[PDB]
Amino acid sequence: VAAIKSFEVVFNDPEKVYGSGEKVAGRVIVEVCEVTRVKAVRILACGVAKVLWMQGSQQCKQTSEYLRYEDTLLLEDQPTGENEMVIMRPGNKYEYKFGFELPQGPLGTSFKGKYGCVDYWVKAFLDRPSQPTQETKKNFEVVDLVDVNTP
């Protein structure tokens, strides 16, 4: 797709379910079918409150984010702090490490221990000059949810 063979978020431990204060670590990986100039690879990691009305009232009460982390990532084995466009060539994996820590408190709420009131995910964005930005999105799972009516 416009030179792009693959674009994905890969967690270092694909089976890990994350709790309070824990590091979420992974890579954004790009592969191309032909030479292409890349301006940036960015991430947005969010924990978004879901809104759910049941039993005649709002249960998942929604409101504000638990997490919103934005960054521009560095290609593996490039100099730290450097601002440089990348010429991606076929036959190579272009890997960008990321890592963020989750908040110390509860990571969200749950209704009747069945309906999780929060969505966590990582989006990545592939920016290229005079070309539409491409997006990828991957969900991740959390624990440390508390009941909606917890004091």
Image (spheres, rainbow, N blue to C red):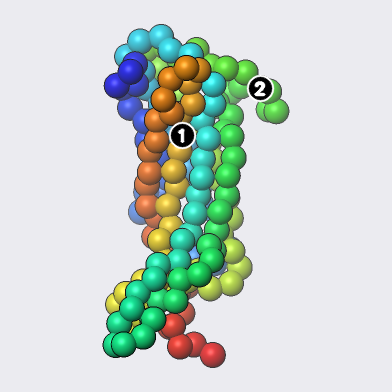
Identified at 39% across, 35% down, the residue is 135
Which residue bears the numbered disc 2? 83
Location of the N terminus by quadrant is: top left
* Residue 98 against residue 79 in the figure, above or below: below
Task: Inspect this view and state whether residue 1 appears.
Answer: yes
Location of the C terminus by quadrant is: bottom right
Label 1 is placed on what type of residue? Phe
Q: Position of residue 21 (x, y in %)?
A: 58, 63
Q: Position of residue 27 (x, y in %)?
A: 47, 37
Left or right: 50 in relation to 68: left
Identify which residue, 80 or 148, lies in the foreground. 148
Which residue bears the numbered disc 1? 125
Identify which residue, 26 or 73, lies in the foreground. 73
**Residue 41 — which label?**
none
Q: How many marks?
A: 2
Q: Position of residue 8 (x, y in %)?
A: 37, 35
Which of pointers 2 and 1 lies earlier in the amino acid sequence?
2
Left or right: 55 in relation to 45: left
Identified at 34% across, 16% down, the residue is 3
Viewer-nearest of discs 2 and 1: 1
* Callout 2 secondary element: loop
Left or right: 80 in relation to 140: right
Distance Cα–Cα, label 2 vs label 1: 17 Å
Identified at 54% across, 66% down, the residue is 64
Identified at 59% across, 40% down, the residue is 71
* Residue 100 against residue 132 in the figure, above or below: below
| 10 Å crowding of disc 2: few (<14), some (14-19), many (20+) | few
Label 2 is placed on what type of residue? Asn
Quadrant in which residue 58 is drawn: bottom left
Left or right: 64 in relation to 121: right
Residue located farthest toward the right when viewing the structure as drawn? 81
